[PDB]
Length: 166
Ligand SMILES: Nc1nc2ccc(C3=C(C(=O)O)CCC3)cc2s1
Image 1 (cartoon, rainbow, N blue to C red):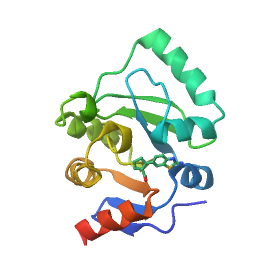
Image 2 (cartoon, rainbow, N blue to C red):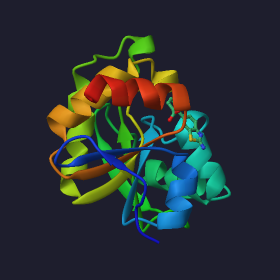
Image 3 (cartoon, rainbow, N blue to C red):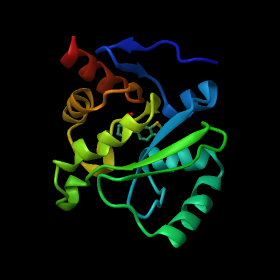
Image 4 (spheres, rainbow, N blue to C red):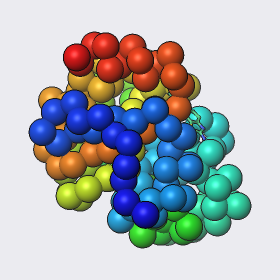
């Protein structure tokens, strides 16, 4: 299957009201982005959901990556297997502003997307990380230069995001 049902916000950013787990299972994109933490512990939010959809194969692989390479930096990323969701998973660490991490690092986090021509992604630093989701979409639009398909689960949030752009 291919991406379908997205609204084009800019020349390279698309958005859909969808559960990113269901989009990944259907489309099996070349790259799905995980909203990760520095130790790749996929406990809640989108990370917990993507890891559960791989039946914990993502966490076992992530633990081996950490033991061999050490933790990521905030604003950094690594490429691991996408398992059943994608060819690759790009694990990207946005700042956790609820813990005093600098919001400037949200631009650095999205810059990691530019190494891939097409990605399926969530909004970074939204949810448990505490950033305003409409600010996260603005940083995405201002920073990502490649084609990004953003999936937003919550209908109320999706409608707010689309209204801020159109
Ligand atoms: N299967 C899924 N579990 C989750 C968990 C969290 C989310 C989040 C957002 C949303 O797109 O609505 C914004 C903040 C967190 C999405 C999904 S899809």
